[PDB]
Image: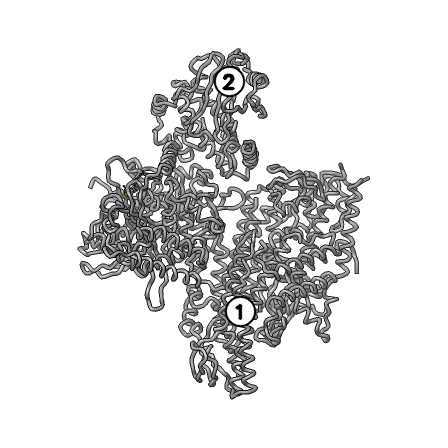
Amino acid sequence: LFLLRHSSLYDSFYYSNYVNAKLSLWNENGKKRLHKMFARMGIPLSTAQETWLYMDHSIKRELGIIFDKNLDRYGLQDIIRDGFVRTLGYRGSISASEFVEALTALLEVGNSAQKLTNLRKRWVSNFWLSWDALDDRKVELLNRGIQLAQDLQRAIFNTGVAILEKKLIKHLRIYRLCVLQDGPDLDLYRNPLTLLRLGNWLIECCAESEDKQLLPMVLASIDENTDTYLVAGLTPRYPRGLDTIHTKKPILNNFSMAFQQITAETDAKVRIDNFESSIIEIRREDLSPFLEKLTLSGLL
Amino acid sequence: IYVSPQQDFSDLMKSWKNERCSPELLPYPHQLMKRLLNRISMQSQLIENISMGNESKLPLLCMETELERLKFVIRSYIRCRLSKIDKFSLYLRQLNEDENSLISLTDLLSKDEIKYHDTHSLIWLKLVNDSILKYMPEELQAINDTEGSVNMIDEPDWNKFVFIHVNGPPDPLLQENEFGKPCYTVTIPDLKEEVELTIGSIYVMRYEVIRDLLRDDKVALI
Amino acid sequence: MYGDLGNKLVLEAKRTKQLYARSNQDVNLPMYHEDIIRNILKEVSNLRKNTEYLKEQQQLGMLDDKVAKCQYFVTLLCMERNKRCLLAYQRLRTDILDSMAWNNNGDTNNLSHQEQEYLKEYCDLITDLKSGDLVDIDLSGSLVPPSDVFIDVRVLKDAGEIQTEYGVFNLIKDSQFFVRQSDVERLIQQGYLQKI
Amino acid sequence: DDNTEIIKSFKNFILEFRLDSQFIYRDQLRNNILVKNYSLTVNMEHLIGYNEDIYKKLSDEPSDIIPLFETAITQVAKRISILSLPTFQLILNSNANQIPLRDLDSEHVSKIVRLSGIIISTSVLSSRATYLSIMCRNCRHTTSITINNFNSVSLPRSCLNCGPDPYIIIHESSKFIDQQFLKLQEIPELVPVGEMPRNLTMTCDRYLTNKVIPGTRVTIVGIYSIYNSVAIRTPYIKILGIQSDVETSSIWNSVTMFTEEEEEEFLQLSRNPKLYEILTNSIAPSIFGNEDIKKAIVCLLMGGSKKILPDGMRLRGDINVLLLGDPGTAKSQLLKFVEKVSPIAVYTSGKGSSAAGLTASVQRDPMTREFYLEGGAMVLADGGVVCIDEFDKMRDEDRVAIHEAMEQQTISIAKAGITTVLNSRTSVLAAANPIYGRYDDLKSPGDNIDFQTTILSRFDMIFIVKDDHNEERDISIANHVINIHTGQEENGSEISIEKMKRYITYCRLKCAPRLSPQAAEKLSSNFVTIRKQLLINEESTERSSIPITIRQLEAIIRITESLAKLELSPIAQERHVDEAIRLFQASTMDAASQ
Amino acid sequence: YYDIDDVLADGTEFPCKFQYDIPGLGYLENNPGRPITKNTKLSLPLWLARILAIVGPVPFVELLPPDMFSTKVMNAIKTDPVALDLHSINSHFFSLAIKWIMLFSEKELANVVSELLLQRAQELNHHASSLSIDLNANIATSTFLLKLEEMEKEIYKKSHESYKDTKRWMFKK
Amino acid sequence: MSLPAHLQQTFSPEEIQFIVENEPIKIFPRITTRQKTRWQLITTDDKALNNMVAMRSTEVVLWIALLLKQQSKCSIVAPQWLTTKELDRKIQYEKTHPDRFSELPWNWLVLARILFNKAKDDFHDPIHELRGKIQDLREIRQIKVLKGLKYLNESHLQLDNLSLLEINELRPFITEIMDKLREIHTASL
Ligand SMILES: Nc1ncnc2c1ncn2[C@@H]1O[C@H](COP(=O)(O)OP(=O)(O)OP(=O)(O)O)[C@@H](O)[C@H]1O
Ligand SMILES: [Mg+2]
Ligand SMILES: [Zn+2]
């Protein structure tokens, strides 16, 4: 669940990739199913939306049993897991996943060639906010990171809702394709990490499920201040928590090789300077020929 | 009388504390400061010689830290002295202008302090003469007039209240009290009082009455 | 009356002193109040004219001793008051300039020509003092006692590979160093680095 | 038994809590005792962190547990302050979800709840009993009673033969505290569909009294209890903590409340070389153009300086602005933004207003049969801005009641044996339309304005806004509105509403500039020139409908003083005089020339 | 001599009464260039008043009792030193009182002023010691601060800064 | 001028700490410097450091001790007065005598802070108990200081056993108030 200990239980179930994937919370049916689940668990809606600290202690203590008996009905049996929780005297307790989420949020939104250099300088600066958050004396930074993580997850959820409602995810035999052109929050997706977050959200939702053959996904975004794309190849994922011989085997990311070969053969002034070779920057005009060549290559 | 570097450092610390907490400008320890500067030079040369040439890493760090501490102490002492000289330039000049006075700035100040005093006095006098003084009549053209409505020479606050700690001799002036503890007796002329200072006790006295004991090193400003 | 202009100038001096006290790190002296000082000097000249006229009247006139004494005393006291106000204002400004000079190792449009010359000469004097037997010490150094030998610092403003006496520090913006406080103390003083 | 253990647990919490190396509550208690502030503010998150059982006990039965906490606080204070003091007050802070005022029902009885609303009425301080000294009529037996103000106490029914109720209170030996009653309404945005706003009765004690003024949004933490005025109980709220976004203490007192870190943030902002542009851009960011009107609104918010002469004559220091324009000019939106940003403001409609609504109303108490005076928008908005929308719609009778308020800044009432002169130091921002709904250039200005000159002279600046159909401006406005609909600089080019409100309060409470002789000379020259031009512009057919009197000179002086105050400058120079003159020429002379 | 507050204190106006007929001293009076008759009552700055009073047999001027050292003010000081608002009475009250005492060699005013200063310094130290704490991360303090004289303000600032620095050093992480 | 205004007539807390770190302290060396390079210090004595044996009590300067502790080459022996029993005895002495101050070391506050921040595992007793005891002692001494501040006069004043940090904190207020009282009395004569 997303930041269970620093938000409400309703928010924790709502803004979770796995819960949305297994319930489709991006439409009204998913919300109705979630409300029905909460009603059968015996937790009032007002109680669920209460913050974690002030939630009724009886329900908080019984939460483990309540989940043990009710999550199986709705297919959320995988929510049960064992993690590491760290506490300091007279302070709140924070789990490892929540700490990592706060650090990533600080890294992402913490606060021609010239603009690119300025953006990369800003990211380098955010690195130091993330570094400072690792200290026990700087807890205000951690709280700020938690709030930014909540906001970023909300924005990514809105963008994913927009993508899925419009049916923007074109399906080609070799691979899937999704291109963002006129979203409300296009600026947030200049950072590769936010784009990867959105890509993971989309991969878990409606793709990990539906019993559809695994297919690599292409996610692209556009920034008007520079008029270029940020293409990011994403490897497919097996259903979460499904131990199997084929699930035991890993899935490799072949997009770096195909992108490099296309760039070398073609002439579109593509950038492969990023460490993650699957993320490239493409000029506005060249994306259509690049995708044509990608489809015709068949090396994905 | 040279004894050992530790005693020199202790005396330097005592002088620094007294200068920081004292109202007046105390006499300069010429010999002690010369010894300290020479020792700093030799120690810096020794550190350089050792460094130029892993068990020896920690000692070198200790030497460098010690050198930095000593340099900071000397720097703070000298800067406080310079500020005091700034505040009493006219006083100090008046001291020097008088011949009956026993004190002379050569004993009361070092050569660097004398040069700084003279240069700053000349510069400030030039500024105020080119700005203001040249327009006033001859009667008001003196930067240091003591016969005016308000005296222009700022003397030290002799009766300033300071904290002291009585330590005793490192004693004709020493005498015992009723309770069998050693004590000192000082008088306050204005109030016609007698104050009994007990060794090892902290007091808040006027500087003038404790001046002799402080000079003799029987008490130390906290 | 006569001392109102001087009183206003001293009020402005008090305002400047309060501004200096309130300011944390950055202090910029206000503009030299040339007009008020000009008016004060004109008033002093008028008082001098009054004194000369009184003396001439006493030389040849019907003025008596008591009237002459009282008028002369009043004029002299007014001149003393104006002189005191001017000197207090100038001394406060000079003290602030002195602190500024010591803050540096050794805009100006607000200063007057006399104040600019004074600042230049004082900086020269500070350098001369630093050139003497106190060369081993750096008089214009930090007044905070040394506490930690090694500290973490972060680059605040980009700069090339500045070659300091202690070593070469390629100050790339947003990069941390684990170095001695003494070596990079000056860089922190100028604002290139930060202790964090 | 259990009470002693609860008190011990609270004492241990007070004496042992620490998040790094400062005992927060111990030091806070010592500091509060130093300044004779017998109270203690406790953050509930810290209580939860220290021990969840204590929080559970506190939440289960607040009315029975809080007094034990107060006793523990008193004991710790005595230990920490006296070397071997009335009962201390407990003020709570929490971040729990706010319950809508209308959602408060039976389910929330005798529980700690957090809610926000608007204060509409406050009562006069009363006296409660804490320590009572009593004596029996017959045998004269001395006894004492200790009373806590939390209600789930009476004089003994039986003496300790004596008849029923034999004890009589001795007053000179008793101790009392302060009590106040407040009326809290629900926020307009939170009201359900087609329902009148709901009122709630609330009470505060000791250090929570005289903390809020009517018309200010507040957040309240308290206990949802009930009192029997036969099968029903009247609900009410027992206030435990008040949190408001307006420093009421600094508004009704010459005293000013601002942290050192605040004072130094507002000085740095004032030091900005171009603060005027930042504030002009910070007002109505969603409205295109209207820069001059935004500057006028800035001047109105800042206000001028008021002078009281030795002879007793008082000079107004508030700036009034009128907006006469065509439909679609965004005047009402500007009025709403002004009401939102000003520290104190009331938004009223001329149509839906009355003489007694906008000044003060004689009201008879139902019980005492005595007449009292309630207050209206110009008493509730004292020290702020009154936004009178639809100014033109107002009846003559109603309108005429505003003159003294605007000019003399007082309200004179002689009704039902009540003879008093109230204080209304307010600024009026009004919007209106011409007679025919548009400013027809064919007809004379006199025919386009039904306002008598007497009311118009009081407005410092009059803006005649005419909608001109220009293709470029139309395209720009359409693009701006489309971007607004389909769609945060905060890079020094604009400051949020809260910061602007705080800066306005600080500037008003800190600076009151004065004109220099050069400013006075320039202003006199400009006034002579303007009056001469107005005299020349006169036509034999009609006399100028827009007036130019001494009030306009005073208005220009006020604008200059407000401009100087904007930068915390003690003196106003010719630089501000030029801007004030430009604004006057752009608005009032522009209206008059047409 | 160069201390700003001392210069301001000497500029305050004190009542005076001339004892001689001095033609040509009208500029001190409201009107310029007219003779000033004896016994005329006017207010002069302290710097001119003191010297004229001491110098001048019958001196030139007689210093009348000011309004800042009147029976009403003394009674208020004795009744409630802490609640008394000294700023409205004068912003340099202690400096002017010390100057007046030095001028007139009187002990009653000295005793009253000493008692007032001690009783005010008690509350001054209380307020200076009182420091704020940020739980998430007044009225009486400001009410008393509005009543302080300039010297008391300086002492308060010094003590408050010392306390703040000590607390910061103690609780530095 | 040369010296800032806040450093005039008083010491900053950092200066008080610097003064404190010149005092000796006992340590347990975790290395064997003694032979069966060489420290050559000019401010303190270097004989002790050279003749240092493992797990043998030796005396060195506090700042040198902290420098060694940073390298985990010496365990600082906490002062005897910094035990729970001794602090309790001092609290009892303070409570029984409301007129005097307990005979605590002149550097107890500064040394306690330094040792708590730098040497946390060296203490035999729990740190929180020591912090609570120190806090209680500080409040009692503050009460005594407030009670004793009522006797300021133009003549002398005695504050026995008061520590260095408290004197540094109180120097401005006490000094200025007594100076003004003396000025008034002098003017009276
Ligand atoms: N420049 C502008 N920028 C943005 N919105 C505008 C602008 N001008 C007008 N509007 C919009 O036009 C509408 C006009 O309504 P509004 O109540 O603000 O008008 P008004 O000027 O008060 O006119 P009326 O006299 O008819 O009451 C509002 O939605 C306002 O948002
Ligand atoms: Mg409208
Ligand atoms: Zn009875």
Report whether B198 appears left or right of A61. Answer: right
Q: Residue furthest right?
A: F36
Callout 1 crowding tier (Cα within 10 Å): few <14, some 14–19, many ≥20: many
| Tag 1 residue | C40
Above or below, comparing residue F150 to residue C167 in the picture: below
Give the number of callouts: 2
**Chain of residue at mark 2:** A
| Tag 2 residue | A289
Foreground residue, B84 or D266? Answer: D266
Measuring from the top left, give residue D566's x and y in whole percent. Answer: 43, 53
Quadrant of the rendering where the N terminus of chain D is positioned: top left
Above or below, comparing residue F127 to residue C3 in the picture: above
- The residue tagged with tag 2: helix, strand or loop? helix
Rendered image coloring scheme: one colour
Q: Quadrant of residue B131?
A: bottom right
Mark 2 lies within 8 Å of ligand 1 (Cβ measured)? no
